[PDB]
Length: 23
Image (cartoon, helix red, strand yellow):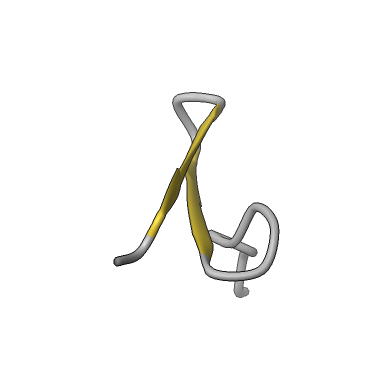
């Protein structure tokens, strides 16, 4: 299956529970 590695718009959310924008 597939999972959402995206937090907000342009945010790389990890299974670590943290969101880092991709800049």
